[PDB]
């Protein structure tokens, strides 16, 4: 659960 | 005249962090501490302001955007991130309502899929870093805070595009973290850095750096883009990647790692010394093997990178990226490798072992980092030294290739040429 | 010859009788095939009760789906031609594809419905410490269901109905970790050729190339293939252990967390510096391993305990959900229960030890932040070891600073039906 | 793809 979404799952 | 130098990946990064020297950056800042670059360049400020605007949301929504996948809306309440996302398609009026009335922060994902300049910038960075480079845009209305203090799992370069924002950076509780997490202010201590970002400013910090920001009261909202990279790109990841290759690629000669563990081993309440010494033996043997030969191992990391990165930036259509141009190479031609930073060489887990060449020239820009069939060229391992020649040479004569026959020399170059990887000079 | 269900060991011992376990593991296990031919009419009768063609009649009435529960196939030209329909499988349709089209039927994980196969496989999971699945193969007379090939698991084949002609070949990939079909021309001549009849048991290691066919006649062939040890090699355990070491690294230790050199993935040759750095990490890890023993996280342990069968229960799983007998007091002596269904590990203001068990696992989903367990302070580890290794131990003898946490530790384990007051 | 479906 990251706040910044580097790579969308 | 041009804000950033797009001549090469290196020139782009050099201009991106100017005046800071790249040598100083990697020696003193990268993965060590934050780097704040406050400027007062009118031209740069205007260029940054063109990377992404709050007003672009209207046009973006007409293209079909979804909550969660493309955009999130949130506000910081009681040190926790409150989500104001709706279901399905996101409409511009919904975003504006939560933004203007609920004082919510808007977070747009992977804008490089639609914004051309961010595509050009991020593609160059992927080449320079050799790692995936995504980005998120954060738009926060005046007098508010969208997210509570926290840290992320990636290296970030933050560009302030519109308005100003008040930032506070804290020492990491988990240095170079490979996981993200919210943090309670009552456990992060005093800020190591506190400042104001304005259009044209750039901020870098390593994964694990705790941070929080809020837009000052007034009529101006804040807009910034966070360009991130180096997710799961540590020595630990690479070490597991290599060991996996060394253990699941070896031929049928040494069955020792293929034999089964003792029965009920997983039911033991202690790490059996029998397995302990045995595992240590394998590790030492593997270490010797790694130094024993300059082998070429399979790498899931290489494959993950090449298949998900951005394709080369194209002003018009992808002509020179899919359709070979100029003149066909011959045994008497002088060839030069093209799109070198968009190619990887590896081996898969045929009589002789083969070497595979993969490139991202045909990768989709529209699905970059969205986590939504991938063929490459094949050559016998004997061609490796020839490939190194083409790689480590500005221009090379086809006849000079370290191959036994001329047909191999021509064939090799022809194969690479068909993928637009060769330029006949 | 009758299977003895008194313990995991007794079960396996009887299963392979008259072959001794000492012999099995010293000469056959993961080495070469083992054919056990018997002349035990009772055993042959027992085997027949494990599974038969007509059982699908009741099974399909329950509702069985193609692909998921059943698969219809037939070997044509060295390949498997599938005759599966999309949806629910009706016994009449299967019978049609079987008797008319000469197709072989393959039922997946019969233990989900057959209590005997459940009772057997569950004891085998305890004995091996690995997941144990099974597939039923029903082939009509004078036909063949599959082309020559090899699998990635250790198998125990039990001939249930009729006879079947088996041919085993030398493995192309010894103790393979992947399955693969082979060309009839690349396998050579059969190393073993024989006929399996009801009551017979056949074992062969992963990698063993094989192919079978039901002889001409009226009677069909029915056998169950009980498999285990999938991805349970030292290589797997090595990666499992290293992952644990790498990712369970302390907050103050950052070397393995630092980034690799930029563009390293774009290189056409392993740099000598990266190779040296890697060799250095490996040797360090090696030393760290033999150095101070300690519990490390293990995805293999978690995968096993989360997907294995729950203890066999004649009727309702009452004994598995609600504890029985008297509550353990500080003066009583206790004995751990369902020991082979318990695993102790660690997670990726003191450190904690976690205990997981499979007493509440679903039999219906076998092999087809949602799994919690019991948490305990690392300070209780030595006490947990005492209980685990003891046949019967008094609560007072537990190595804990206070008597309260001794009654607390036992009570906690008792509520989960893991402790019985001896 | 395995012919024997050990684990679905
Ligand atoms: O602007 C904010 O509220 C936080 C932005 C942030 O967390 C980031 O850029 O990683
Ligand atoms: O009997 C057959 O068709 C093949 C059975 C098989 O391959 C197995 O039991 O692993
Ligand atoms: Mn952040
Ligand atoms: Mn098979």
Image (cartoon, coloured by chain):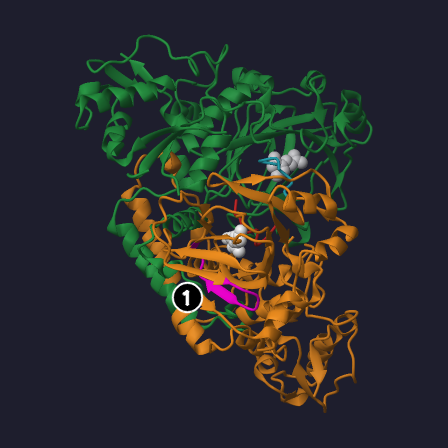
Chain colours: A cyan, B green, C orange, D red
Look at the image and tell me in which quarter the C terminus of chain C lies: bottom right
Q: Is residue C32 above or below residue C398?
A: above
Tell me the residue at 73%/28% (across/down).
B141
* Residue at the spot of label 1: C289
* Residue B412 forms part of the magenta stretch: no
The image quadrant that residue C321 belongs to is bottom right
Residue C45 image point, x, y percent: 63, 70
Given residues C61 and B174, the one toward you in this image is C61
In the rendered image, the residue lying farthest to the top is: B326
Q: Is residue B133 above or below residue C314?
A: above
Tell me the residue at 72%/88% (across/down).
C330
Segment colored magenta: C196-209
Helix, strand or loop status at disc 1: helix
Q: Is residue B404 left or right of residue C342?
A: left
Residue B43 image point, x, y percent: 53, 15
Look at the image and tell me in which quarter the N terminus of chain C lies: bottom right
Tell me the residue at 50%/43% (across/down).
B232
Chain designation of label 1: C
Residue C375 image point, x, y percent: 66, 68
Is residue C123 in view?
yes
Q: Is residue C201 left or right of residue C328?
A: left
Crowd band around label 1 with a 10 angstrom C-alpha radius: few (<14), some (14–19), many (20+): many
**Would you say the beta carbon of the disc 1 residue lies within 8 angstroms of ligand 3?**
no
Q: Quadrant of ligand 3?
A: top right
The image quadrant that residue B216 belongs to is top right
Q: Is residue C235 left or right of residue C410?
A: left
In the rendered image, the residue lying farthest to the bottom is: C331
Q: Is residue B347 left or right of residue C335?
A: left
Q: Is residue B214 above or below residue B56?
A: below
Given residues B97 and C231, the one toward you in this image is C231
The image quadrant that residue B224 belongs to is top right
């Amino acid at each position: 659960g990251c706040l910044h979404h580097h790579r969308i799952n | 005249p041009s804000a950033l130098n797009f001549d090469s990946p290196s020139s782009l990064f050099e201009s991106l962090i100017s005046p800071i020297k790249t040598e100083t950056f990697f020696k003193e800042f990268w993965e060590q501490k934050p780097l704040l670059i406050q400027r007062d360049d009118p031209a740069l400020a205007t260029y940054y302001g063109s990377l992404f605007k709050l007003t672009d949301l209207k046009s973006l929504c007409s293209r079909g955007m979804y909550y969660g996948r493309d955009v999130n809306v949130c506000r910081c309440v009681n040190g926790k991130k409150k989500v104001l996302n709706k279901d399905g398609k996101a409409h511009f009026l919904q975003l504006r309502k939560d933004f203007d009335q609920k004082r919510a922060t808007i977070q747009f994902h992977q804008p490089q899929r639609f914004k051309d300049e961010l595509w050009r910038i991020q593609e160059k960075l992927e080449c320079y870093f050799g790692s995936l480079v995504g980005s998120n845009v954060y738009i926060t209305p005046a007098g508010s805070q969208g997210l509570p203090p926290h840290y992320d799992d990636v290296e970030v370069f933050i560009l302030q595009l519109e308005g100003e924002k008040h930032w506070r950076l804290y020492h990491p509780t988990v240095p170079l973290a490979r996981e993200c997490s919210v943090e309670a202010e009552e456990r992060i201590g005093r800020p190591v850095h506190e400042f104001m970002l304005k259009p044209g400013d750039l901020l870098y910090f390593p994964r694990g750096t705790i941070h929080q920001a809020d837009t000052p009261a007034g009529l101006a909202h804040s807009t910034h883009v966070t360009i991130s990279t180096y997710q799961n790109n540590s020595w630990g990841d690479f070490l597991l990647d290599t060991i996996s290759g060394l253990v699941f690629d070896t031929a049928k000669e040494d069955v020792e790692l293929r034999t089964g563990i003792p029965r009920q081993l997983l039911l033991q309440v202690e790490s059996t010394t029998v397995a302990t010494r045995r595992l240590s033996g394998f590790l030492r043997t593997l270490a010797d093997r790694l130094e024993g030969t300059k082998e070429l191992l399979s790498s899931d990391m290489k494959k993950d990178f090449i298949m998900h990165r951005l394709p080369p930036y194209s002003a018009g259509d992808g002509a020179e990226l899919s359709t070979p141009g100029g003149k066909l190479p011959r045994l008497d031609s002088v060839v030069r490798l093209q799109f070198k930073d968009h190619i990887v060489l590896t081996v898969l887990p045929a009589q002789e072992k083969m070497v595979y060449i993969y490139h991202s020239l045909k990768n989709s820009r529209e699905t970059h980092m969205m986590g939504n069939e991938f063929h490459g060229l094949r050559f016998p391992l004997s061609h490796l030294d020839a490939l190194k020649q083409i790689w480590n040479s500005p221009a090379i004569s086809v006849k000079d290739l370290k191959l036994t026959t001329d047909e191999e020399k021509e064939s090799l170059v022809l194969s690479l040429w068909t993928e637009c990887l060769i330029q006949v000079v």
